[PDB]
Image 1: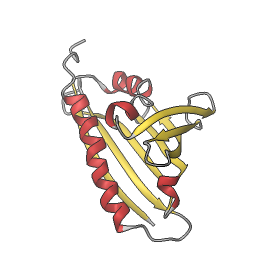
Image 2 (image 1 turned 180 degrees about the vertical axis):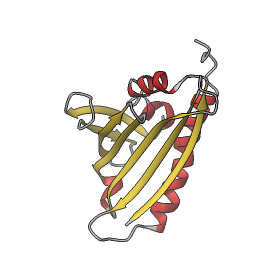
Image 3 (image 1 turned 120 degrees about the vertical axis):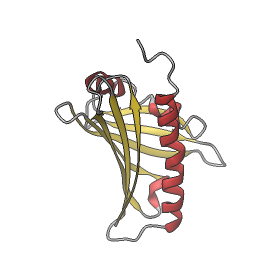
Length: 160
């Protein structure tokens, strides 16, 4: 069982530069688009290319929250980046995984780019998702992706 949600940003930066930039700022997404919510991200197993698992720590509240991420695939020839949450208390109730898909995307002007952001939410075994995890899911995701957007769009120094 699967649900999905998405958003798309823009930049004066061309795709191949924004590519290589987002790759180096991927673990940096966590504090810069969800600052209060996560507490740390940590490299668990693998060398930082796709395949690599991260151990993730998230907010206090009688018991601090636990997850694991993994980088999943990266391509230049169609300019994509991918990760998923593999494990955690935030999945455990109904979800196998929440994958993410990112595109550095051709703009109608060839000198700039679009930066597309995607998330998808997949159930544990043959189960059904919570409508409460849909409603939380997309809307926490407007929280994430409008801070990806206003991070990108409100970046003042992009002429460099």
